[PDB]
Picture 1 (cartoon, chains in turn blue, red):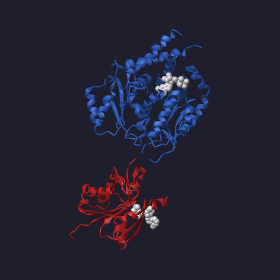
Picture 2: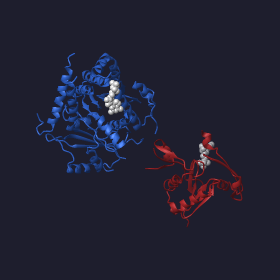
Picture 3: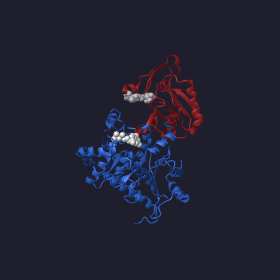
Picture 4: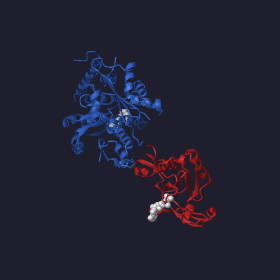
Length: 369
Length: 176
Ligand SMILES: Nc1nc2c(ncn2[C@@H]2O[C@H](COP(=O)(O)OP(=O)(O)O)[C@@H](O)[C@H]2O)c(=O)[nH]1
Ligand SMILES: Nc1ncnc2c1ncn2[C@@H]1O[C@H](COP(=O)(O)OP(=O)(O)O)[C@@H](O)[C@H]1O
């Protein structure tokens, strides 16, 4: 199985280019895309080596980089121009899909704040038209900005099969808190570490989690509640890493309860004490879970790249993510009373209201029906 | 026989030769290399065989020991792996390059007695031993190995340091 990545807008190209640099250095791949001498299954993200990227001014600075051998602002303006080059960009994808052995999914890296955001919304719909059996995971990044943000939300709630949220307000606070930057090329260092760590169990094979659906099938309970948040602690026993991930200071998100948790421990930790820690974390009751259906916490180990110590990443599904949509929602209404049909905004405003209504009702003892 | 076998260890810039005194030839010969990952330490042929996953070190590259930590590992390898003997149970005769710094001679001595607990030891100049092998105590020896060559005048068993010449041209250079 293989996973084709797409990079849209200024953000997608930058965080994708930094994702590939980190992923090339994590492996034994020279900047000239040639394997150096110096186990890690790399057929999923690299093609025999060529990355399976589809990039869409910034391209020139990439081509002037040492990695050249590795390959307006409205939403309506970003939607229309994609329609006029509909056939163009798909030929690149159609040859890469059929040239691929057995396609699995489509990773999308884009910022929803505007030509790239508009182009993304267009492409997300067409992929549902052509390929019905391919997952679409989107590494969206949150910030007329309220308008564009909610429109793409209308597509991300019914088209994208999964979604991992990364908001700049939580990342920028971290850079000033634990990095003391006072830049885009600086916070992207953290975004690259989370992205590279997200697909760790795919490149280093283990007994479990050898496919992208294996990670997603546990967290997302119903096709509607497909939003996730992240947590990265080291900015050492396994009990220490678990307790530091469940603190609010580390999450990348600005009653409520958890639906499912996945922990990625990438160190050389002792794999015999991992089952012990899950016995004791349950006793302190550090996290509150859904009352309707059963839920648990998941811990998965891996191996760090020797060519480059314990780290940790936590993928969670918390209903407190509903607050982020509320801010965009409330920000939209204030502009709607202040200034060919303007009916698409009405439908998008309505459908996101149902998503928020699902979350607040997802925390009740009678979410069934 | 009352005496245990004495060991003879020839420390070469490229290949070490080890065996038992009295024998006509060394029992083992291996590369003077120590390797560690890019089992924690690899020495000899194994280091060479698995050089692909290791970073190699040559502690006696030009005849003179430059890294004693790895030289100690080569000697450990010599006793326990190649000869399969316990150094604390056998006297050990070691060889040294011509013009070997005095401090190095003391270091080798200290390591044999304190680290390997040898019951006895001795160190002889390589060129002198070759002259002995030819049945002579006087003559000039042209010793050309892997990483260094020397012309060593010897009179009555004693090398004449003032007349010894070193040539940084040997087998390695010829191969390249
Ligand atoms: N997280 C993150 N967001 C970025 C980065 N660069 C740009 N963005 C986002 O992208 C938005 C600007 O989009 P822009 O590049 O003007 O769109 P375009 O002109 O259509 O490509 C801003 O609101 C930023 O939040 C980055 O390096 N990291
Ligand atoms: N028959 C031969 N003809 C030429 N060179 C040889 C021959 N046999 C070995 N060599 C070379 O001799 C060198 C090793 O000789 P040696 O005296 O053991 O050196 P050292 O003691 O410094 O390791 C190597 O460069 C090897 O290629």
